Length: 52
Length: 53
Length: 48
Ligand SMILES: *[C@@H]1O[C@H](CO)[C@@H](O[C@@H]2O[C@H](CO)[C@@H](O[C@@H]3O[C@H](CO)[C@@H](O)[C@H](O)[C@@H]3O)[C@H](O)[C@H]2NC(C)=O)[C@H](O)[C@H]1NC(C)=O
Ligand SMILES: *[C@@H]1O[C@H](CO)[C@@H](O[C@@H]2O[C@H](CO)[C@@H](O[C@@H]3O[C@H](CO)[C@@H](O)[C@H](O)[C@@H]3O)[C@H](O)[C@H]2NC(C)=O)[C@H](O)[C@H]1NC(C)=O
Image (cartoon, each protein chain N blue to C red):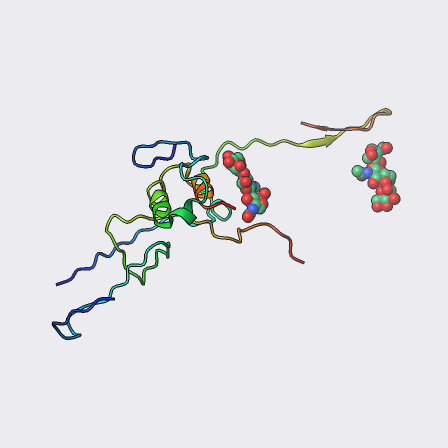
C-alpha cells in the first residue's frame, strides 16, 4: 500500500528493515511525510520507528 | 569552517538547516516550503467515562 | 521585498462524537403500556 517513489510495498514491511531511522533519519522522515493521506500511515509509522 | 578574506560581517548569514527532526505545525514558526509536508502523531490522554460522588 | 501567506479554516471538534446536540422532527406518537390484570385466581402483568 505505502509507496516509496516507485516501490508500492506492503506497509507492514518497509524496505528499510531494520533500523530505518538509525540508518537514515532524513530519508525516513521524507518517507513518512508523503503517505499522510494513506490509510496505512500508522502501521507504516510503527514499522519505520522500531528496532533493537 | 570557512573564511571569506574579502568583506565585513554585515554581509553574510548563518541559517542553520539541521533537519532530521519533525518539530510542530505552530502558527508562531514559519513553513520551509509551500504545499507543506505534514505528519501525524497520536497525542496521549484520551477522554473517557467515570462517575463522580 | 517579502510576502506572508496567511491561511485558516474551521473543523468539527475532537470530541464531537461524545458531546453534541441533535435536531429532530417529531410526529405520530405511539404509546405502549404495562397493565396488571387480576380476576378469579390469576394475578399477572402484561406489556401491550
Ligand atoms: C461514555 O459513555 C457513552 C455512553 O455509553 C459513550 O457514548 C457512546 O459512544 C459509542 C461510541 O463507541 C456510541 O456507539 C455508536 O453507536 C452507533 C449506533 O447507534 C454506531 O453507528 C456508531 O458506529 C457507534 O458505535 C454510542 O451510541 C454512544 N452512546 C449513546 C447513548 O449515544 C461515550 O463514547 C463514552 N466515552 C466517552 C464519553 O469518552
Ligand atoms: C399480584 O402480584 C403483585 C406482585 O407480585 C403483588 O404485589 C406484591 O405484594 C407483596 C405483598 O404485600 C409485596 O411484598 C412486600 O412489599 C413491601 C413493600 O415495602 C415490603 O416491605 C415487604 O417486605 C414485602 O416485600 C410486593 O412488594 C408487591 N409487589 C409489587 C410489585 O407491588 C400483589 O399483591 C398481587 N396481588 C394479589 C391480589 O395477590
